[PDB]
Image: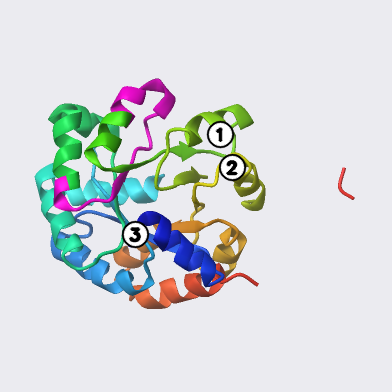
Amino acid sequence: MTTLEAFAKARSEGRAALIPYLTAGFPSREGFLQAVEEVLPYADLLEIGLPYSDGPVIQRASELALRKGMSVQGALELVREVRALTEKPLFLMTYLNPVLAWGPERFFGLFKQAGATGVILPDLPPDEDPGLVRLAQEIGLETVFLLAPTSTDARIATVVRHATGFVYAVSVEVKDLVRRIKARTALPVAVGFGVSGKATAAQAAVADGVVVGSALVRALEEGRSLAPLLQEIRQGLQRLPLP
């Protein structure tokens, strides 16, 4: 199930893909693995975050995961164990600092080896280091880059020529942003707008995919079942002159 196939399946079913995002090792290593099991039935693709020292909800999750010993090596084994559970696309979200510490070629090589389909690099404007981007892609990883509501048409054009797998629009109104990105690329467009239930999901349903991250941190923090929450979101992702 390639990334493209995952998005296509959701579209053929008349819904935006649901992309759970879980921070590796949060609330604990075992807690993370159990969360993975609970969200898989709702996942078209899965995002796994690599905890890093430097919104507040995700920062909280990364903080605790780190306090409990999560590391790059710990995340690599977790990616392997998640890959053993599913054939679905798995994307590792990581800031650049840890990648530079391990060495890009080694870092990307290890995660590709571990079973990752690609990486999401939030703090790397692809146009600023195409060499690094090509390195990850040559290794076999899809590379997702970010766009924000402030992105000009030129910056959308610039980012979509480096992104593979999908492009991610984050608002740390959805229809307008999705329209402007889709006008410049056929790549699937995923959005992150703090979706937490049916109503908010319905507003984001226009996107090819919707990431659910902060809402899961809260559910995990409060010790609540994840299925009810994801079910409400799934139901909202199902699709129905101005001056």
Q: Quadrant of the C terminus?
A: top right
Sequence-wise first label, 2 or 3: 2
Q: Which residue is mark 2?
A: 181
Residue type of the residue flagged with mark 1: Ile
Q: Is residue 7 above or below residue 146?
A: below
- The secondary element bearing badge 3 is classed as helix
Alpha carbon separation for disc pair 3 and 1? 29 Å
Coloration mode: rainbow
Q: Which residue is mark 3?
A: 217
Q: Position of residue 3 (x, y in %)?
A: 37, 55
Q: Which residue is located at x 60 percent, y 27 percent?
A: 154
In the image, residue 58 lies in the stretch drawn in magenta: no
Q: Which mark is residue 180?
A: none
Q: Are marks 3 and 1 in contact (CB under 8 Å)?
A: no
Alpha carbon separation for disc pair 2 and 3? 28 Å
- The secondary element bearing badge 1 is classed as helix
- The secondary element bearing badge 2 is classed as helix
Q: Which residue is mark 1?
A: 156
In the image, residue 114 lies in the stretch drawn in magenta: yes
Q: Position of residue 192 (x, y in %)?
A: 48, 51
* Residue extent of the magenta highlight: 113-133
Residue type of the residue flagged with mark 2: Ile
Q: Position of residue 13 (x, y in %)?
A: 52, 72
Of residues 43 and 54, the one nearer the viewer is 43
Of residues 212 and 17, the one nearer the viewer is 17
- In the drawing, does residue 178 fall left or right of residue 140? right
Is disc 3 surrounded by few (<14), some (14 to 19) or many (20+) residues within 10 Å? many
Q: Is residue 234 visible?
A: yes
